[PDB]
Length: 289
Length: 293
Ligand SMILES: [K+]
Ligand SMILES: [K+]
Image 1 (spheres, rainbow over the protein chains, first blue to last red):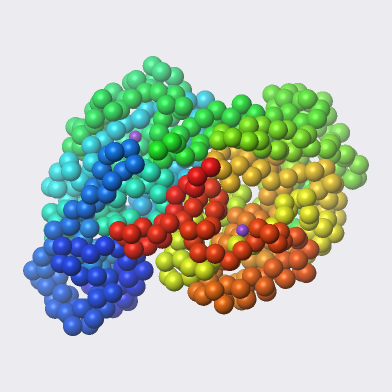
Image 2 (cartoon, protein in one colour):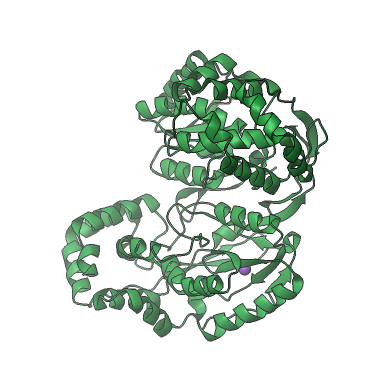
């Protein structure tokens, strides 16, 4: 089934070209993206054999700390360029499968989708009267997700045990989500060939629960806002959805950072919101950083 | 639909109800007649059939747009041309029929004022081009489209597809009325533009001629309304593209290049759709983020 699709010459050549295009910092092995071509010419068949027999061992991600202007630090986990290549090859096959399942109001790390589309959808909801915002803050997905629960969800769709095996090994390696979009940055995420898709597979369960409740929401990776018509309803939604996230998905809601507010109080994907009194419409613009 | 008999599609109950709903959803400031968007429904109950019949015989008279000055969030003033709500309604009714026709003609690297497209998509496509080595940027600055477009040239282009003379007639009257493009995207703003039910589509119909020419020449570009950047691999090639494409825009489309603001530059010198570009030292890549305003 899927492993041979992932390892096909066609898919691997596409993954190689993408990873070279994406460049990026070296992982723990010190290998630069400019060395991948020659490395694969020598070792590509060995690597394919190891993957086929479940003996390929991903390298741990390299932890990189980047200063944020507000005095915080952004954490990045950089896979080796070989692992970015394999992750890309996996994602190229898994992405079309899951695109058929995903909700139209999920916008993070998906083909032809971006943060601005989430903003515009949320604005339309706000301007329809749903201007009480439920802003649920989750602890970092890959710091808190239970690997068994995630792999079980993935297993509902993906029956190839060889693919299951290697995806689990990448979770263990420390793959994570580059959150630079929170600073309004646009561009290729570092270390994100596969981890954002895996987060979306899990969080698609939240999308389905919110759709079952008839809620108006947008989501970008693990950052969701829900648009509601009244404070009382927003408080109920906050309580019910936070309970679902913790009990069903096994994720962790930071209740202190989560809040109900009006749009002026919301910071989302680098944007803030304001009421344009000429247009008589909420609009959005980059918030101060 | 039949492109020779579109006026009755524009005036159909279904199309007009949709246009009414969208104009009310867009809200907006009043035009020169002082009519609020909440007053449109009662006005159309009395005058809707009158307006339809006037349009059928080319006797409907658009009102001039209202010049409205509003603050920009970060300082300074934005000038808008606000049609009356009746004219926003008719403009929307026309655009609802013309948009699906032209969406099938448009280039995938045109992103301004189109359904499900946005500025960030143009930025992402441009970054991919820059990171593939095309980091000499041709930045042609055009004077405001509706201040400079030749009405006959624009109607000629539209008439290649739209054969309904009654639709041609009303679109031309809307040009004279002063419809324009809300430029708040230049300030990184996301939201409903004012006065833009029809004007941005008309600009895209014209500028689609430029897109086809650039594609014929194999150029890497993105465009958002009348703001286009072209990604080239060398300074020499950029200067050549600048010369050739500026000539095409002025000679074939009749638009106006601003000499002093057009330039060839590297990504760090480009301001586009509210974004600047920078070289991320860790990623060894160009990325974008909002520029200082
Ligand atoms: K949130
Ligand atoms: K330009």
